[PDB]
Image (cartoon, rainbow over all chains, first blue to last red):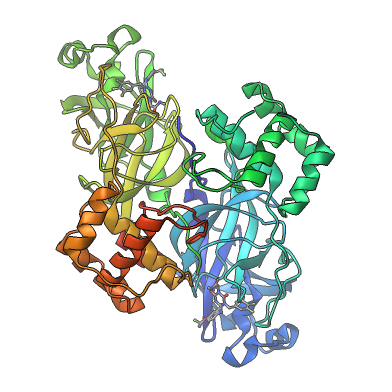
Length: 298
Length: 301
Ligand SMILES: CNC(=O)Cn1c(=O)nc(Nc2ccc(OC(F)F)cc2C)n(Cc2cc(F)c(F)c(F)c2)c1=O
Ligand SMILES: CNC(=O)Cn1c(=O)nc(Nc2ccc(OC(F)F)cc2C)n(Cc2cc(F)c(F)c(F)c2)c1=O
């Protein structure tokens, strides 16, 4: 019993984390086979951070301007792919796990290994929000910390951290260096956009609560279109049939149909929680996917 | 910035996790140097698990009755012994991946990371607090017995919890690494249940400081208080007493924020007396007590 926000075990990723130094700029890098992946912001200096020309900044450096440590790696090739740098090194990481690069979709979750100076400090779970931010915990030096999921022995890397926006949320890229959302790697004013709640995830969590003995919030039914109207009023993402489909195995296990759980959610939205808690939380929680629930509950 | 329940990176502990099997009973063990540590419950068969005679079950065993598997590697057991509620299995191989480590027995209020494991295979990591009633609010299914809790300091792992059982309210009870249970619980079926719990007061104040450092300020009021007057309020709200030692522990956060500990106490006082009025603090609608002052410093420095 019990339900908690749980990260994947970080050992496979820990052995991949390096420090990347270019002149007087340092951050975190990801060493896999004979290649170190890191954010291209590593080539800027204090002066450059406001509107850097990365192409032009990069030309002013060769293979030997980049210091990789985790020991020492000798850099023998460099290239910029989108917003990340690929540094070919002479040594294949003997600690390289089976891995894949994947671009996740909004509302999916992953584990973050928060790192500083190439050294792992902590691990936590979070969601790619609908507005393509994450609500992490990062301080200066955490650039290049990565997010991932694990499938038995394979690590799917989906996120590399770049920056904190003025609002205190975080943005970054896939491991091919394309930002999630409309963000750019420069210190300018950047609007995140409306942060909507991941409806399918909130429903999953309500299933998790029923599996764990929290049932006071059950009852009425509703309709998709009727529920979706309430969704928009409360800045919840619209609920589609594919979402109803993804929730099938939890519905099946609990004997609670999706639309009955929606009608339960309507009352919570329209009426609040009347001072009660669900899985020890006094608000609706949207960072567990249906898969997350199933995994933890079996 | 931002604030999250954050576990320690688990790799150092992952490499110590093994599977221990005795007949058809299996669970997790911890392999450090040439010793494997696990719950003694593993020597029970189904028919013994209700009211076991551990001394009796143990004497009937030899080394070869214990199968220890570290991933694919079959270890060979060359000694066995029982210490309180754990078993200690001497094996012929020292664990090449043994971190620098210590065993520590923690106080109520302190937090640790749990690596939840099944069949000696790690499945997830999350943070927990030892509750004042000596349970933890974890996430554990059957087969998690022997999973460990720990803290890490530089390269040194401090092991503080080995998981044994789930109580009927769905909370969790276990031992330190010398095998002595936290709280009054026993490794057998009895009428045992979790006491009434209280809130870890010094942790709430640390988390309020954390909120301040992240830009939450609405709860900061014009009042101050005394330690005496504050403790009267705490008692009413089933909060643990705040001691002058606690005040001293909170010194650093006070120095970083420039809010005197007694001024923060008066803020908490108002929060307890009037509730939060539907506002949030660090994305929470309740007062959180599972961050230590250490946890806060770690994450806001
Ligand atoms: C709260 N902070 C964060 O979430 C992450 N973050 C960070 O870690 N570092 C930043 N700038 C910086 C400063 C110094 C430095 O090296 C020096 F110590 F030698 C190296 C770097 C990368 N930034 C700001 C940032 C702004 C951007 F526009 C970016 F594109 C970017 F990658 C980072 C962080 O946000
Ligand atoms: C929700 N469950 C838990 O948190 C932990 N838990 C557990 O993982 N296993 C249990 N019993 C069991 C069953 C079969 C078995 O071998 C077989 F699987 F091959 C091995 C074991 C240990 N128990 C019950 C328990 C009761 C006690 F009195 C204990 F002392 C104890 F250590 C475990 C769990 O609670």
